[PDB]
Each structure stands twice: as C-alpha cells, then as structure tokens.
Amino acid sequence: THWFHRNPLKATAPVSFNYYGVVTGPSASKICNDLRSSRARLLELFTDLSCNPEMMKNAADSYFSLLQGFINSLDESTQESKLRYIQNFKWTDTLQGQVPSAQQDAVFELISMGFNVALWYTKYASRLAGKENITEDEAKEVHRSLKIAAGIFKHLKESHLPKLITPAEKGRDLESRLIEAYVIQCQAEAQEVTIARAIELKHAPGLIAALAYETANFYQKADHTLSSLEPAYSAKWRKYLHLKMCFYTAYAYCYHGETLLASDKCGEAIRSLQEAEKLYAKAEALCKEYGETKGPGPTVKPSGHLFFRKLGNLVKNTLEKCQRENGFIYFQKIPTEAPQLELKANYGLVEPIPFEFPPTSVQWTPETLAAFDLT
Amino acid sequence: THWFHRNPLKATAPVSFNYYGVVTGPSASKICNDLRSSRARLLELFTDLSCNPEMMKNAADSYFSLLQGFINSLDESTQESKLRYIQNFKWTDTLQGQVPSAQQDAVFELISMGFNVALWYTKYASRLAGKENITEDEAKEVHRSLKIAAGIFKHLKESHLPKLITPAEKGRDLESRLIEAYVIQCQAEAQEVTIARAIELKHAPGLIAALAYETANFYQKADHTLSSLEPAYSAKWRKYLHLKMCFYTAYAYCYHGETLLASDKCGEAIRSLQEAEKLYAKAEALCKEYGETKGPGPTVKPSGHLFFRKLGNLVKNTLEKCQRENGFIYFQKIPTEAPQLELKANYGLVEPIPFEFPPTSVQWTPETLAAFDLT
Amino acid sequence: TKNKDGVLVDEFGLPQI
Amino acid sequence: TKNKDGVLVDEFGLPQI
C-alpha cells in the first residue's frame, strides 16, 4: 500500500463580491452573485470526502470562467481587465501554517485557487492510493490524478507567476522553486504507482531497476529544490523526500542484483543485494527521524514491505547459484564497493498532462462589464 | 577418508654382536646369535607390507627381552648390566634426513628401536585408515594401533630418556619435546577416527563439537611443543599441525552452531557458522602452504569434503529460521566476536595404552653373563 | 499505443506483452 | 562397557545408541 506525505490545503477569506455603489444595473449584479456562489461551492468541495474529479472539474471551471473576467480583457482592445485590482484576496500557505498573505490582484486569486485544486488532486490521489484492495481501475485513477495535478502546477508556474505584480515571500506556495518541487513530487508519485504495477506484473528486473532509480532521482531533485528554503518550515518535508530516495535506491539495487545474477556475476550481485538491504535499513532509520521532525502535514508510514519478499527470493537463488564460489554464510571475493548506478528508464516515466484554464465566461459582456463603474 | 602426515622411518646399521675372544662357552655365543637374528628380523618387518601387529609384537618382544641383558642387572642388589657400554649403535632420525648418530650404549639402541616400533604402529594405522571401504573392525584396529604407539612413546620419554648418558640433541628423535609431540599426535589421530565415526552414527552435535574442539587443542599443543625446534627440519610438520587445528576448530564451530540454533540464539548461530567457514578457508590456505613447504616426509592431501555438505545444510536451516531477525544477506545484530568455545568432551577422549618392555630373557643367567669376559 | 521505437505500451507506459 | 556415570559406551568410548 502507498504512502504519500501531504501538506495541508490552503485556506482563504470569504469573498462576497459585494461592491455596492460601484455596481450599476442587474447584469453586473447577477454576475457578482455567481462569482460569490461559484467560489463558495468550489471551496466547500475541497473538504468534501465524497468529491470526485468530475465534480471538482465542473466546480473549478465554473468559478474560473467567471473569475477570468476580472483578469482578461473582452474585446482585447485593452491590455487586461479593469477589475483586476478591485478585490483583495487572502490565502494561507502549505508550509506557513496560520500565517496568511494577501494581495489585491485577481491573478493572485487565480493562482492560489488553482494551486489548491492541484493540491486537491494529489489528496484525492493519495486517499485512494492508501486503500488495501486497490483494483487496476483505481490505480489508473490515482496515476491520472497525480499527472493532472502536475500539469496545473506546471502551467501556473510558467504562464502565470510572471504576471504577478508582487513576488511571494520565499517559503510561500507562489514562489517558483516551491511549485517546481510539487511538480516533481507528483511525477515521482505517479511513477511509484507504475513501479508497483511493474512488480506485480513481473516485468523485467532491468526495467524496474531503471524506473526505481529514476524515481529516487526525482525525490533527490525535489529535495535539492527545497534546499534553498528555511529549515523550520521545510525540514520535515525534505526528510520525507530523503527517505523516499533511500527507499527507491534500495529497490534499484535489489533489481540490479537480479540483472548481475543473470549475467553470472556472483560477487557483484551479492554486493549489490547487500547494498539494497543496507539502504532499506537506513531508510527505516530516516523514517523515524521523519516521524520525529517538527513540520507541516501529518506523518505517514510505509509498513507494507514487498521488498523483503523479493529480496528473500533473490538471496536464495543467489546463494544456491553462487556458493562453492563466494561461500555459504561467510562471503569471499566480494567487491569492496557497491556498483555505481547509471540507469536509463525507457518505460514508465511520467509527463504532466498539459493544463489550461477555461475561456472567459460568455456571461461577461461589454454591457455587463460597463455596468461596473469605479468612482 | 583419513589423511595423516608421516615422517620417515628410522634407519640403522647392522649389528653382528660378534665379540670374538670376549665371548666363551656355547650359551654366550648362542645369546649373541639370538640377538643378531632377532634384531635382523625385527628390522626386516618395518618395511614389509605384509606385517601385522601380532607379527610386530612377537618380533619386538623377542629381541627386546634379549637386549635387556645389556641393560638390566640379573642379581639385583646392583644398578645395572656390565654390558651396557660394550656395543656401538648407529641410527638416523625422522627429521634429520640421511645423517646418522651413534652412541655406544645399550639404552640408546633400546630407545631408538622402540621408537621405530612406535613409528611402525602409526604407519600401519595411517595405511589402513586411508581405505575408502574401511569397516568398523578396521577402524577399531587403527584407533587401537595409535593408542599403542602413544603408550610406547610415553614410556620411552618417562622411564628411559633420563637414563641416556649423552645429553639430548635438539632436532633428534631422542629428546623430550619431540617425543611429546608424537604422543600428542597419536592421541589426536585416534580422536579423528572417533569423530568421523560419531558423525556417521549421527551422534548429538554437542558431543561432536566438543571432541572436535579437544582434538584441535591437542594439535595446537603438539605444534607449540615443537615451536622451539629449528624451522629448517620442523616447518612442514608444524604447518600440518596448524592445518589440523584450523580444520578441527572449523568443525567445532560448525557443530556448535547447530547447538546454538536449537537453543534459538540466531545471531550467535550465524556468527558461529561464519567462523566455521572462515576457519575452513584458513585451513585450505594452510593446505597450500603445507604442500609447498620443504621438509621430511611426503605431502598428504585432504580431498573434500563432508564439512561443506554439513555446512550448507546448517546455513539453509539457520537462514530460514533467522532471516526475519537478522538476514537475509546483509546481516544485522551479529556479535563482532565469535562465540566462546570452552567445551567438555565426555566421550571420545583417548589415552595412551600403558606399555612396558619385556623383562630380561630367561637365556640370561649369572653364569651366562660370566661367559662374557670383559678383561 | 506505441512508443518511438514502435513498442506496444500500456496505460502506464509499460511494455504491453 | 560403562563409563564412570554408568552410561554404556562402544569401543571408541561413544555412547551406545
């Protein structure tokens, strides 16, 4: 069963979109009511455990198609919307606890809400990934959800962050590096699901070894991305990434050893299996430092060792094959160093699904927009 | 199959026992022909493959009882025989190659010849212990022959060596340490036979482990006893004793490990078997060095082996039980030091069979002695 | 679905066998 | 033959089975 660390959802101040005098005429007034309601509904859905990706997709597009009117021009004879600065938006952040941040920009709202949707996808994903039975249909769903979240994060980062007038404090979700980390964790996580599938389907060891190794590199890269932050808020997360890295380095060594065995290198294979078991033991160390490290989001546990099942199988086959050469329980002619892994994964690597916001709601007409009078 | 290292048999120059004018009467000159022929016959047998113990005993006994005339006094009320210094004897030594040594003393002949008879018993045994078919009766015969040799050796050392007028020479068969080595080896060898039997009869592991352990200590004792000899002629032999010690220490750890496994001490059992395989490997390297080492006596080889069958078996049982706690491959919580062996063997320990030379031949009387005129 | 080398692949990107 | 403890042993001094 899967274990994925999760930081808490962002929270936001209620927005009524009630502008009083600024609003003149029924058209502009109804569009403000629909903004109010479509935002409220989307926010309610975040904490709803009966929410699936169909409902979230609908609610999000409804709200975003309206919100877009505060951002993009209609006739496009104007740079942007005149309402972009009308409203102050306040959001908490995944690592920052109860200390919120506020900007009066519609873009900040767009990015923050969109960031929370992606977040919601990773949570729906891990909620499902943690169930026991876990049919194949549910696995695609988890895999797909994680890739959708990736696309949203990536899109927000490249096509949106630059538009902001106010750069976010380092350590906030709207900082570029933080978003890159979320992208990479989403890919790494989707690949975990593919690794479990590859293993139950009994694919080639080299394929699984390459995928495990590439996955550990993503975690290492995500960790390197969060390295530029402050230890107080970012420490727990980074420990989890380091832990994952040990977990999947241990898998790579396990399945590499089967490769070395099939090529009749007994000493090298033995050494490589020893490394797998060592790394996994150190991974069980880092696991406790992780559970004892103060930081945002609850602590998760691996349990569930399918590793020792494979290892026991490799060991018996290796000892039967390699004894009379390297020895029975006391091993001779073993390389002093573990093999240095360079592995290319040709199968299983995950791309984020390209994402785009819906086009501005047709409910935004020049007449409606004109009924907004700022003075 | 058993392999016992053997130093060469002692060689001697012929003795006619012809004193010419000194000997008068029929009885004195008869005694001289009885010595001549009995010694000649006894020497013939040492190299005669058809010779059994019953043949060796009757011959040796016949000669020795006659030779006793040259040593003991008949009349009592006196220390010794007037003939002790009448004859010069010339002998080679097991470790000294072709270079002989001579003393005109009857006791020197007595001890040298007795030594060779002891040697013959150990060679008879080693010859017979080298069969593949060997039956239980034959096994007992080897075991017994070795105990006889031991007792003969011990008797020479305790009751006889002190009598020689010539001080002992380091490197030659006639000194304390060297005979001591022989006594110990014989006991050690008889025990090897018992150990081999205990394993065939499926005796308790503790029993076997303890006997193997004691047997190794004997080899370590013999090897230390010879430590003061000059390496030139002692090196091959000592390399062999060191080989036997490691070989039988490995056995101790092996069977001791079975003992630990049953008592459910997993980390220790694993550690015990590791030490066994290590010692056996050390044993194999000493085997190579032993074969290369220059020295008296041919190289014997141990083509193996059942240790590995027994070791493989235990490693399988030990890992199956102990992997959860320690294994599978990289082992955890294993004692850095090998488990302590102080083991009491209550069964299988060998003691030399007490030996005495025959009393003076009845052919010796105060009158027959006077027929020897020494003036 | 096939990859660039013409290998049949599944929903997860693994070789379809 | 019996050893000091009254245990029956064979000619090699092992316990009889």
Image (cartoon, coloured by chain):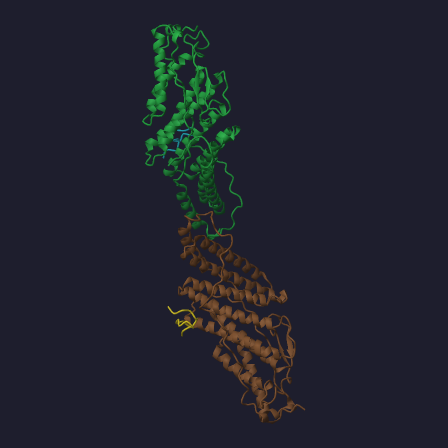
Chain colours: A green, B brown, C cyan, D yellow
Q: Along the line of sight, which residue is nearer the eye, A161 or A35?
A: A35
Residue B237 visible in the displayed image: no
Query: For residue B11, what is the image quadrant?
Result: bottom right
**Residue A68: horizontal and vertical position, in percent?**
40, 14
Quadrant of residue A349 within the rendered picture: top left
Q: Which residue lies most toward the right here?
A: B375
The spot of residue B35 in percent (x, y) is 57, 85
Residue located 59% across and 67% down the image = B226
Q: Nearer the viewer, residue A49 or D10?
A: A49
Image spot of residue A300 (x, y percent) = 41, 35
Q: How many marks?
A: 0
- The quadrant holding residue A35 is top left
Please tell me whether residue C4 is drawn above or below residue B67 in the rendered image: above
Q: Which part of the image, by quadrant, shows the C terminus of chain B?
A: bottom right
Check the image and report above or below for A216 versus B37. above
Judge whether B279 appears above or below B328 on screen: below
Q: Is residue B285 above or below residue C4?
A: below
Q: Is residue B87 left or right of residue B307?
A: right
Return the x and y of residue B69 as percentages of the image width and height.
Answer: 58, 87
Residue A191 visible in the current orientation: yes
